[PDB]
Image (cartoon, coloured by chain):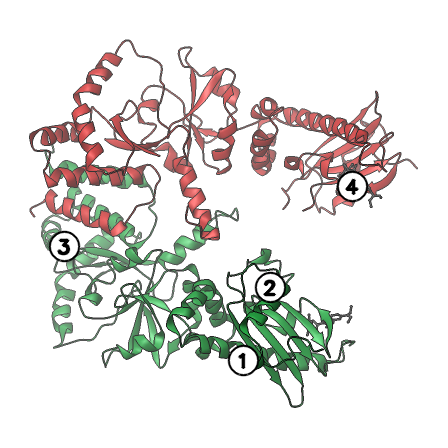
Chain colours: A green, B red
Amino acid sequence: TKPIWTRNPDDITNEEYGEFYKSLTNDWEDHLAVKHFSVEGQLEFRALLFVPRRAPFDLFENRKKKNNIKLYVRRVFIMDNCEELIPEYLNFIRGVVDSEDLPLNISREMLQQSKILKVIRKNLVKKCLELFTELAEDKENYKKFYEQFSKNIKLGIHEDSQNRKKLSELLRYYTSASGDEMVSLKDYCTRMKENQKHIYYITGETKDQVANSAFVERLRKHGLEVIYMIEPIDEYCVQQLKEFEGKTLVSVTKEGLELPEDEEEKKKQEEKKTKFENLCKIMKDILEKKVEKVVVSNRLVTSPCCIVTSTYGWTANMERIMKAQALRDNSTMGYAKKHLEINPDHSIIETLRQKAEADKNDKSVKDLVILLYETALLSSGFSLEDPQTHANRIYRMIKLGLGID
Amino acid sequence: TKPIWTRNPDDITNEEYGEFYKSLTNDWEDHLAVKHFSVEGQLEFRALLFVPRRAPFDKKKNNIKLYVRRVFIMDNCEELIPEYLNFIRGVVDSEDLPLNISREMLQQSKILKVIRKNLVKKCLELFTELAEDKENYKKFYEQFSKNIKLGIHEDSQNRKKLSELLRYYTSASGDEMVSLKDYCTRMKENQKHIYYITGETKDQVANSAFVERLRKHGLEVIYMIEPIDEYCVQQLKEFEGKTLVSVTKEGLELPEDEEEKKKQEEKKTKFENLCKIMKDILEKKVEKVVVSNRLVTSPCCIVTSTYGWTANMERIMKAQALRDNSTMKKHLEINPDHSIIETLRQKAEADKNDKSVKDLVILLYETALLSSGFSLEDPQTHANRIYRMIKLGLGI
Ligand SMILES: CCN(CC)c1ccc2cc(C(=O)N/C=C\N3C(=O)CCC3=O)c(=O)oc2c1
Ligand SMILES: CCN(CC)c1ccc2cc(C(=O)N/C=C\N3C(=O)CCC3=O)c(=O)oc2c1
């Protein structure tokens, strides 16, 4: 009688859909979700789409399967891999597309097919984003989905600038407040204190490393929520996600960390600015060019120091990923400028300011400046120049802790 | 009027060779080296082989054009040459092999197996020739060092002839690369082992902790900085009788001393108390804690089990496991003659529940992992521990 995608959506049982999706992809378990829609107008076409349970494989990047949408015209099969029928970041969708009107045999000149496809393209991506917007309403079944295709969503953020807002509403992250849960961007905004003009994120490799890192200290004490961006995609994602609902994004690993001045803590921070600037310009010289600037931390509580990164430059996470990639492709590392922030109110920083402003030539002072700098790189997610150099330096500091002999 | 490979070699100008290799591979510069040979016997066939100057970017198993009685057949010939020689370009003109076969007539594979084994011999002949001019072999090993080490891994029958062609940086060779036969000439007749280290840069392995008592003892250590080496040594057991030992692995055998081992034995039992304590302070963070016989300036180091993943291995594999996202044995050696070990034995045997002792054992263990090429559990945890130790260096 009629093919399965011509019967209309609410007249089909979810198991009938599944038997079809199994027969279409040989997947051993049924579909996860289904969107099934038709279109009339200048163009008549139907479309049945499936989202597999287990995220498909990355396919050699061969790009030899831009998609797996079986393509029909007037109920006859045509192609299996239709390059411009679906944007690359939705290639996991399985299903069929049955057009009534598109032109098949075409030369270069007949761009009309490429118009019909572009409109079907936008209509297919629209009905998908609709389905994901639908899925986001049941919080704990959307979990089975974002678990598999989070990497896919973030890719769209980078490529499809036209749908960037609708896509960003679908992102979920770990934050400081959501101790064990993932939360939307709209939720983080509902918990913002007014006059906070920024959304705080940190990029590392594990939650425990970014949660207990040095960079977030005076931000968690300040009652602020910070977003944990742990997957390597995130480093590229934020590069094109400028703002959400008006508020701009800021990295807690970068210099110039803006915070709300209350009862002009800038006046106390300014006294610290000038009080320790002596110590600032000394360690800049003890280190020479291993660092670019030495400034007073406005973000450090329990740790004495941290290594922050240039504003318009690579980060510790990026520097790790890129150079972990340059192992794979045999290459010189080629051509990341760091800033070191010191906590004025820490005893090690206070006591160091005394020994240094008394005798800045003391080889013990030089040794301690280098040592704190090296451990700060460890805190900030970097790799050391020469590990045994730091090792011998720690051994010397241990010699000082107990009997020097 | 006659094809170029059937013409007798030494009647061939190197420009004719180069012009031909250009016409065969469109390479803009001439060949690097050429081996050209014929064979008679049960099988008659000729072969002209080229080594390109620039190492190519390697599913085309090789580019050896294959002729029979001077007629072309195919170029991608899978079982004509082992995979680690895919950079060879050239032609092979057989007189007798059978092309059309029923799967039963594997006799087609015998003729190929014979040409295969015969081709690899004439190549290793060429490479042994190249090893004689030191600073031109460098132009080659610079490009194909990776290839030779792969052959060590795969071709066990030619494993010996290949190792003779390996070149490395060592402690003695400050800037030059040296053969294995040379390292044997500098061995003491009481030395039964060849010492190597696996790292990432020459500068890091030369100043490493594992080699301390080896440069003081007048011993030479081989610097393996390329990642292939990690797999190379897994199949490179011995050269010229003397076996290889990794300075990152446990059970470091050394030339037995003038019965001074009794002093190493007194150190063994004297610090064994501290060994039992640090073993428990680090709850399964390490597998065993024993007395070092290899450390001079460093107080402690982390070696790996003989059969386990090397320190190098765990770094590379987990650096690659960023691709899969798949996310996946240690020994702690302490230096007896170091003051920090003596002082720790005293603080431990006086009050072994001192949190300063706990702070010191954990701190020493973590920095030793850094010394040994590992990654830290929680960097901010180690940092807070150092900040605590620095706070102790001066008043709290
Ligand atoms: C119908 C016979 N031939 C020529 C061999 C085909 C078959 C398929 C296609 C697909 C094309 C094409 O549009 N590619 C880009 C997007 N795309 C579609 O819109 C459908 C399939 C597909 O890959 C095309 O331009 O010519 C084609 C020509
Ligand atoms: C021209 C006829 N065609 C190919 C279309 C051939 C040509 C060559 C071969 C070689 C075979 C063969 O002997 N393979 C074993 C070794 N071998 C070669 O000698 C060349 C490639 C290769 O794998 C074969 O099984 O079928 C062939 C079929």
Q: CA distance from mark 2 to mark 1?
A: 25 Å
Q: Earlier in the sequence, mark 2 or mark 1?
A: 2
Q: Locate the N terminus of chain A by quadrant.
A: bottom right
Q: Which residue is mark 3?
A: A349
Residue A129 vs A207, above or below: the answer is below
Q: Earlier in the sequence, mark 3 or mark 2?
A: 2
Residue A188 vs A22, above or below: the answer is below
Can see residue B36? no
Instruction: Find numbered disc 4 in the image and state the secondary structure of the residue it sits on.
Output: helix
Assess disc 3: are there few (<14), some (14-19) or many (≥20) residues with their C-alpha within 10 Å of its C-alpha.
some
Q: Which residue is mark 4?
A: B19
Assess disc 2: are there few (<14), some (14-19) or many (≥20) residues with their C-alpha within 10 Å of its C-alpha.
some
Q: Identify the chain of the residue marked 4, using the numbered disc in the image.
A: B
Image quadrant assignment for residue A266: bottom left
Residue that extends furthest to the top in the rendered view of this protein: B258
Residue A393 vs A48, above or below: the answer is above
Circle 3 or circle 2, nearest the eye: 2
| Disc 3 and disc 1 on one polypeptide chain | yes
Q: CA distance from mark 2 to mark 4?
A: 59 Å
Q: Which residue is mark 2?
A: A22
Instruction: Find numbered disc 1 in the image and state the secondary structure of the residue it sits on.
Output: helix
Circle 2 or circle 1, nearest the eye: 2
Circle 3 or circle 4, nearest the eye: 3
Q: CA distance from mark 3 to mark 4?
A: 71 Å
Q: CA distance from mark 3 to mark 1?
A: 56 Å
Looking at the image, which residue is at 68% across and 77% down?
Answer: A98
Residue that extends furthest to the right in the rendered view of this protein: B1
Q: Residue type at mark 3?
A: Ile
Q: Identify the chain of the residue marked 2, using the numbered disc in the image.
A: A
Q: Identify the chain of the residue marked 3, using the numbered disc in the image.
A: A
| Disc 4 and disc 1 on one polypeptide chain | no
Q: Which residue is mark 1?
A: A126
